[PDB]
Amino acid sequence: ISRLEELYNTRHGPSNTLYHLVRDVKKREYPKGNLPPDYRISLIDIGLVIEYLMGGAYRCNYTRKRFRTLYHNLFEINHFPFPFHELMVWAVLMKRQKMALFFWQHGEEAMAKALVACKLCKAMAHEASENDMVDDISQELNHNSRDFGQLAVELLDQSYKQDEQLAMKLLTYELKNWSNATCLQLAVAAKHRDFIAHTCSQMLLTDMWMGRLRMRKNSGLKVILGILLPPSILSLEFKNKDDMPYMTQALIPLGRKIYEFYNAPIVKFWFYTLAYIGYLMLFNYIVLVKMERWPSTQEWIVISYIFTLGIEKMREILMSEPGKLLQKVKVWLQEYWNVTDLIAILLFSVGMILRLQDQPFRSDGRVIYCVNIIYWYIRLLDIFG
Amino acid sequence: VNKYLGPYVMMIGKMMIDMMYFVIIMLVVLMSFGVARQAILFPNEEPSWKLAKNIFYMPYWMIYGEVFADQIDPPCGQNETIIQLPPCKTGAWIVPAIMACYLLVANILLVNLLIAVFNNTFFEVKSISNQVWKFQRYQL
Amino acid sequence: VNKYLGPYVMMIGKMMIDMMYFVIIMLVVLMSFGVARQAILFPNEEPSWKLAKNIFYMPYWMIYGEVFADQIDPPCGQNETKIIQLPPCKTGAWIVPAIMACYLLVANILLVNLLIAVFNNTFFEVKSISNQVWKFQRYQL
Amino acid sequence: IMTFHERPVLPPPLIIFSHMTMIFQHLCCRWRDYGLKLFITDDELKKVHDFEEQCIEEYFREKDDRFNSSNDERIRVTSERVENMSMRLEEVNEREHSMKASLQTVDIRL
Amino acid sequence: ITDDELKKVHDFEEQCIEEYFREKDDRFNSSNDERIRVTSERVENMSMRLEEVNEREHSMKASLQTVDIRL
Ligand SMILES: CC(C)CCC[C@@H](C)[C@H]1CC[C@H]2[C@@H]3CC=C4C[C@@H](OC(=O)CCC(=O)O)CC[C@]4(C)[C@H]3CC[C@]12C
Ligand SMILES: CC(C)CCC[C@@H](C)[C@H]1CC[C@H]2[C@@H]3CC=C4C[C@@H](OC(=O)CCC(=O)O)CC[C@]4(C)[C@H]3CC[C@]12C
Ligand SMILES: CC(C)CCC[C@@H](C)[C@H]1CC[C@H]2[C@@H]3CC=C4C[C@@H](OC(=O)CCC(=O)O)CC[C@]4(C)[C@H]3CC[C@]12C
Ligand SMILES: CC(C)CCC[C@@H](C)[C@H]1CC[C@H]2[C@@H]3CC=C4C[C@@H](OC(=O)CCC(=O)O)CC[C@]4(C)[C@H]3CC[C@]12C
Ligand SMILES: CC(C)CCC[C@@H](C)[C@H]1CC[C@H]2[C@@H]3CC=C4C[C@@H](OC(=O)CCC(=O)O)CC[C@]4(C)[C@H]3CC[C@]12C
Ligand SMILES: CC(C)CCC[C@@H](C)[C@H]1CC[C@H]2[C@@H]3CC=C4C[C@@H](OC(=O)CCC(=O)O)CC[C@]4(C)[C@H]3CC[C@]12C
Ligand SMILES: CC(C)CCC[C@@H](C)[C@H]1CC[C@H]2[C@@H]3CC=C4C[C@@H](OC(=O)CCC(=O)O)CC[C@]4(C)[C@H]3CC[C@]12C
Ligand SMILES: CC(C)CCC[C@@H](C)[C@H]1CC[C@H]2[C@@H]3CC=C4C[C@@H](OC(=O)CCC(=O)O)CC[C@]4(C)[C@H]3CC[C@]12C
Ligand SMILES: CC(C)CCC[C@@H](C)[C@H]1CC[C@H]2[C@@H]3CC=C4C[C@@H](OC(=O)CCC(=O)O)CC[C@]4(C)[C@H]3CC[C@]12C
Ligand SMILES: CC(C)CCC[C@@H](C)[C@H]1CC[C@H]2[C@@H]3CC=C4C[C@@H](OC(=O)CCC(=O)O)CC[C@]4(C)[C@H]3CC[C@]12C
C-alpha cells in the first residue's frame, strides 16, 4: 500500500491531469478548494477519482469500509492479491500508455481491464476538455481510449474463435474487483459500440432475450399463441434448470413452466405490445365515434392506461442510478422518448380535464385528444425498433 | 425467358421487401393523419364502417399528386353571396397544419428514402438476379 | 456539336432501352388495371372500339398526378339533395378503388423509383462511353 | 433487453395490480443490483480465467506472426542482412587476394 | 456416349486436372509473397554459410602465413 502511494505521489515522468482530478473531487466532497502544494494523495483520494470517472453506481475497492479500516490501522495484509489491476489503474491515470499496455498483458481480467481503461480514458478526455486544458491532452486521451477499446474487441474475437460458450461466461461473470460489475455492462458504460455489435455479444443478448426457453424457431408466433392461449404454454420445449442462469440476486412442474414463461423478456415485450395495440385501437374508437357528457367504457380503459403509464414512468424515475431527485429527473430526460412521453401524458391530463367540463371545453378536450393520437402512432415506431 | 426482362422481373421481386417496409412506415403516418383529420372534422358521428374508409380514403391519394384542394381549408363561419356557410368545428385550423406536416413527411422524406434504398441496393440485387436467372435457365 | 449537349443527347439515346423495359412492365400493369376497371364498372357494353380507349385512357394519366378524384369512388345507391336519386351501384364497384390503390402504389412508387435506380447505376459507363463516342464523331461532323 | 427485464410482468392497465404488490412488498419487507450476471463458482471461475490467458497469449503471438509474415518486414529484415554480407564478402575478397600472393611466393621458394 | 468417346473424355479430363493443379502451383510459386519468402530463407542460409566461410578463411590465411614463415 505504501509503495503504491509513493507511485501515485511521484513528480517524475510525463505530465498528467491527475492533480486536477484530485482537486475537483476534494472540492465536491468538502465544498478547501485548491489543494496545498504538499498534499500527499491518499488511495482514498484515488478511489474517489475513480468514482467520478466511472460514473453510475460504481464502488471502487479503495472507498469500501474494508480498505478504509486497514488504511487507518496502518497509516500479507498490506499486499494486493491482484497487483496488476492496481498497476493498470495507476498507469491509466497519469497517462502512461506504453506502461499500461504492458500491464494489460501480465496479470488477468484483461477483458475487464481493457473496458475499464476505455471508460477511464474517455472520461478524463471529457474532463480535460471541460476544464479548458490543452487540447492535445484531450486528443491523446481519446486515442488511448480507442486503443483499449480495440484491444477488447480483438480479445473478444479470439475468445469467440476458441470456444463460443466460454466466451459468454467471460462476458457475464461477476467482476468482484470491479464493483461486482459485468464485462457486458462495462462495455455499455464505456459506450463501446463495436463491442456490443460483435456477434458474440449479440447471441449473448439473444439468449438473454428468450429467458428460460429453448424455442428459437419461427420467432414471435409461438409466444403470441402462448399469451392468447395459456394451455399453449405447456406444449413448448423449455430450457434446463442450470443451462445458463442469468439471475439478479441469488402440478409443480406446470406452475414452474408458467412462471418461467411469463418472466421471459420476449414474452413481456409481446404482452406489452399487444396491450399497446389494444389501447391504441380503443383510442381510435373514442375519437372517431361521438362522445357523451360522461366517458364511455372504452374511454375509461384509455384513461386508465394513461394513468398506469404515468405511474410507471414515475417509478422509472425513482428506481434509477443517482441519489438526488434532481439528478434522477435529469438522467431520465436524456432519452428523447421519455421527454415526449411526459409531454403527451400532460396533454392527455389537460385534455381529459377540459373534456370532463361542459361546452365549449368539451370540444377543446377532443382536439387535444386528436393531437395526442398523432403522437401514439409515432410512438408505435418504438415497437418497430 | 428473355435475357433482359427476366433479371428485371426478379429484381422487382427483390425490391418488394424494401417496398413493404416503406408501406409499413407509410401506413403508420397515413393512419395518424387520417384519424386526426376525420376525428377533428366530424365530431358527431355514429359507429359506422365509413369512418374506417375515411381514415384511408383521402390521405392515400395525397401521395399521388391529388391534395383535394377544395377541402384543404374550406371557407366556413361567415356569410358569402346570400348563404350561411356552416359554423366552424373547433380545431379545424389544425387540419391544414397536420396536412402540411404529413405531406412533407410522405412526399419528401419517405419516397426519397425509398429511392435511396432502391439505389444503394441495386448492384447486389442486379448481380444476384443475373446469376439466379442464368441458374433457372436449366429449369425452364 | 456542343461539347456538353452532344454527350447529353447520346446519353438520352442510351436510356431509351431502360425506358423501353419500363414501358413494357408498365404496359402490363396499366393494361391489367384498365381492363379490370372497365369490365367491372361497365358490365353491359356492346362491342366497340371505345372499350380499348377506356382501357388506356385514365390509367395512363394516373401516373402523372391526375387520379381523377371525382371518379375514384362515385357515390351511388342512395338519395342526395331537390331530392335526386343516384343510379344503383354495379356489383363489385368497391373493388375498383382497392385495385386502384394497388396499381398506383406499384406504378408510381415501385416502377418509377426502380427506373430512377436503373438510370442512376448505369449513368457512369454511359457517360464515359458517350463522351468518347462524341469525341470520335467530331471527325465525321 | 434490460429495460424489458426490469418492467413489471403485468401490462400498463394491469400494471396497477403489479405496482400494488410492489408497494405492498415495500410496506412489508421494510416493515419485517441491476444487471443479468452469471455468479460463477470458484472452480469454473478458474477455468474461465485460464481460458482468458490462452486467448491473450494467442492474440499477441498471432500479431507477431502476422507482422513477420508481412512482405513489408520480409523486405526490411532482408536489407539489414544483405549489408552485413556485403562488407563481409569484401573482407573475404581482400583476404583471399593476400592468400593467393602468399601461396605464389611459397611456390617460388619451393 | 460410346466407350471409346468415354475414353477420350476421361483422358481430356485428366489433362484438365493436371493443367489446373500445376498452373495453381505455378501461380503460387510466382507470387510476390512466395518469392519474397523464399529469397528471405535462402538469404538466411547464405549469411550463415558466409560467416562460416569467413571463419575458415581467416584460419586458412593464418595457416598460410605460418607456412610462409616456416619456409
Ligand atoms: C390483441 C390485439 C391485437 C387486439 C386487442 C383489442 C381488441 C380485442 C379490442 C380493441 C378495440 C375493441 C372494439 C372497440 C369498440 C367496440 C364497440 C362495442 O360496441 C359498443 O360499444 C356499442 C354496443 C354495445 O354497447 O355493446 C362492441 C365491442 C367493440 C367492437 C370492441 C371489440 C374488441 C376490440 C376490437
Ligand atoms: C388491456 C387493454 C389495452 C385491451 C383489452 C382488450 C379487451 C379485453 C377489451 C377491449 C375492448 C373491450 C370492450 C369494449 C366495450 C364493451 C361494451 C360493454 O357494453 C356495456 O357496458 C353495455 C352496458 C352499459 O352501458 O353499461 C361491455 C364490455 C365490452 C364488450 C368490452 C369488453 C372488453 C374488451 C373487448
Ligand atoms: C391491377 C392492379 C391491382 C395491379 C396489380 C398489382 C400486383 C398484383 C402485381 C404488380 C407487380 C407484381 C409483381 C412484379 C414482380 C414480381 C417478381 C416475380 O417473382 C419472381 O420472379 C420470384 C423471384 C423473386 O421474387 O425474386 C413475380 C412476383 C412479383 C413480386 C409480382 C407480384 C404481383 C404484383 C405485385
Ligand atoms: C399505406 C398504403 C401503402 C396502403 C394503405 C391504403 C389502402 C389500405 C386503402 C386506401 C384506399 C382504400 C379503399 C378506398 C375505398 C374503398 C371502397 C369501400 O367500398 C365502399 O365504400 C362501398 C361503395 C360506396 O359506398 O360507394 C371499401 C373499402 C375501399 C376498397 C378501401 C380499402 C382500403 C384502401 C385500399
Ligand atoms: C394500429 C392500427 C392498425 C389500429 C387501427 C384501428 C382502427 C382502424 C379500428 C380499430 C377498432 C375499429 C372500430 C371497431 C368497431 C366499430 C363499430 C362498427 O359498428 C358497426 O358495424 C355498426 C353496428 C351495427 O349497427 O351492427 C363500425 C366500425 C368501428 C367503429 C371500427 C372502426 C375502425 C377501428 C377504429
Ligand atoms: C399492412 C399492409 C402490408 C397492408 C395493408 C392492410 C390494411 C391497411 C387494410 C387491409 C384490409 C383493409 C380493410 C378492408 C375493408 C374495409 C371495410 C371498409 O368499409 C366500408 O367502406 C364500408 C362502406 C362505407 O360506408 O363506405 C372500410 C375500410 C376497411 C376496414 C379496410 C381498411 C384497411 C385494411 C385494414
Ligand atoms: C411532341 C411529342 C410527340 C414528344 C416527342 C417524343 C419523341 C418523338 C422524341 C423525344 C426525345 C427524342 C430522343 C432524344 C434523343 C435521342 C438520341 C439521338 O440518337 C443519337 O444521338 C444516336 C446515338 C444513341 O442513340 O445513343 C436521336 C434519337 C433520340 C433517341 C430521340 C428519339 C425521339 C425522341 C424520343
Ligand atoms: C405503357 C405506356 C408507356 C404507354 C401506353 C399508353 C398509350 C398506348 C395510350 C394512352 C393514351 C391513349 C390515347 C388516348 C386517346 C385517344 C383518342 C382516340 O380518338 C378518339 O377517341 C376520337 C375522338 C373522340 O372520339 O373524341 C384515339 C386513341 C387515342 C389517341 C389513345 C391511343 C393510345 C394511348 C396513346
Ligand atoms: C396481351 C395483350 C396485348 C392483349 C390485349 C387484348 C385487347 C387490347 C384486345 C384483344 C381483342 C380486342 C377486341 C377484338 C374485337 C373487337 C370488336 C370491335 O368491334 C368493332 O369494331 C365493331 C364491328 C362492326 O360493327 O363492324 C371493337 C374492338 C374489339 C372489342 C377489340 C377490343 C380490344 C381487344 C379486347
Ligand atoms: C409496346 C409499346 C412499346 C408501345 C405501345 C403500343 C400499344 C400499347 C398501342 C400502339 C397502337 C395503339 C392503338 C392505336 C389505335 C387505337 C384505336 C382507338 O380507337 C378509338 O379510340 C375509337 C374511337 C372511340 O370510340 O373513342 C382505341 C385504342 C387503340 C386500339 C390503341 C391501343 C393501344 C395501342 C395498341
Image: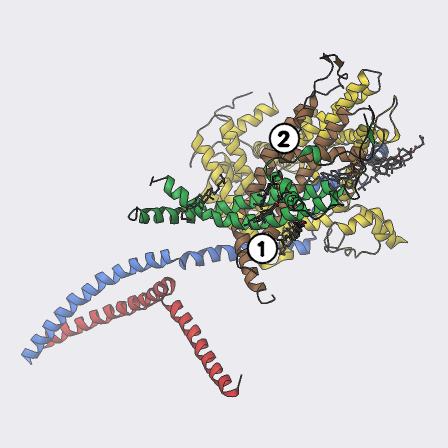
Chain colours: A yellow, B brown, C green, D blue, E red
Ligand 3 contact, mark 1 (Cβ < 8 Å): no
Disc 1 element: helix
Q: Nearer the viewer, residue A44 or C125?
A: C125
Q: Quadrant of residue D2?
A: top right
Q: Is residue C45 left or right of residue B17?
A: right
Marks 1 & 2, CB-CB < 8 Å contact? no
Q: Nearer the viewer, residue B63 or A4?
A: B63
Q: Is E1 rendered above or below residue C29?
A: below
Q: Give x and y (percent) for residue D21.
A: 85, 36
Q: Give x and y (percent) for residue A325.
A: 70, 25
Residue occupying the point 69% across, 38% down:
B27
In the picture of the structure, the residue carrying the numbered disc 2 is B103
Three-letter code for the amino acid on which mark 1 is drawn: Ser
1 or 2: mark nearer the eye: 2
Residue occupying the point 52% across, 37% down:
A121
Q: CA distance from mark 1 to mark 2?
A: 51 Å
Q: Give x and y (percent) for residue A385.
A: 67, 41
Q: Quadrant of residue E19?
A: bottom left
Three-letter code for the amino acid on which mark 2 is drawn: Leu
Q: Which mark is residue A159?
A: 1
Answer with the quadrant where ligand 8 appears in the image. top right
Q: Is residue D50 left or right of residue D12?
A: left
Q: Nearer the viewer, residue C49 or A113?
A: C49
